[PDB]
Image (cartoon, coloured by chain):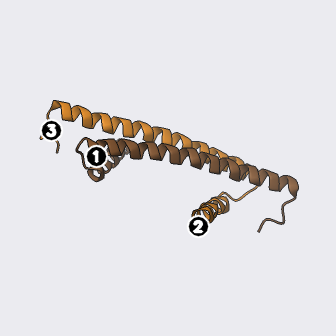
Chain colours: A orange, B brown
């Protein structure tokens, strides 16, 4: 649904999309590192679900500025 | 609600939480970079909302393996 764009505009749009997708990849890599930290926490004997809840509460109490 | 842990276990739990929060900060920084790319796309004349929809569709069509 983008045939209205000429070749230059198509190039700019392709560039935007490729860059966003690359940053999404970086984002996923950080999220996987978070998963690994939570895995280690589980090895430590902690409840990952409760830990995530704890981390969310601390964001909120920090957000309540 | 963690008084049952001794000082060593408390230290390990504090470490887990601090590391997760640090990775959350990195995550937010990447998300802000994504916001900047979408801002540039808007400057280019594109509809950020539609672009996000396009990027989500490409994830899904990639996810449909």
Q: Gap between marks 1 and 2, in whole Å?
A: 31 Å
The residue lying at 69 percent from left, 53 percent from top is B17
Q: Nearer the viewer, mark 1 or mark 3?
A: 1
Residue A10 locus on image (x, y percent): 20, 35
Any mark on residue A64, and which?
2
- Residue B65 visible, this angle: no
Q: Tell me the chain of label 2.
A: A
- Name the residue that disc number 3 marks: A5
Q: Gap between marks 3 and 2, in whole Å?
A: 45 Å
Q: Disc 1, disc 2: CB below 8 Å?
A: no
Q: Tell me the chain of label 1.
A: B
Q: Gap between marks 1 and 3, in whole Å?
A: 15 Å
Residue B62 locus on image (x, y percent): 35, 41
Identify the image quadrant of residue A13: top left
- Local secondary structure at mark 1: helix
Q: Disc 1, disc 3: CB below 8 Å?
A: no
| On screen, residue B56 above or below A7 | below
Circles 1 and 3 on the same subunit: no
Circles 3 and 2 on the same subunit: yes
Please rate how many residues cluster around mark 2, counting C-alpha atoms within 10 Å: few if below 14, some from 14 to 19, many from 20.
few
Residue B27 locus on image (x, y percent): 53, 46
Any mark on residue B42, and which?
1
Identify the image quadrant of residue A61: bottom right
- Local secondary structure at mark 2: loop
Q: Nearer the viewer, mark 3 or mark 2?
A: 2
- Front in this rendered view, residue A36 or A65: A65
Image quarter in which the C terminus of chain B is found: top left
- Residue B1 visible, this angle: yes
Residue B56 locus on image (x, y percent): 34, 49
């Amino acid at each position: 649904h983008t045939d209205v764009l000429n070749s230059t505009a198509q190039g700019q749009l392709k560039s935007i999309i490729e860059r966003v997708e690359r940053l999404e990849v970086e984002k996923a890599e950080i999220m996987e590192q978070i998963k690994e930290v939570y895995a280690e926490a589980k090895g430590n004997g902690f409840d990952v679900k409760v830990l995530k809840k704890v981390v969310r509460i601390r964001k909120q109490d920090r957000a309540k500025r």
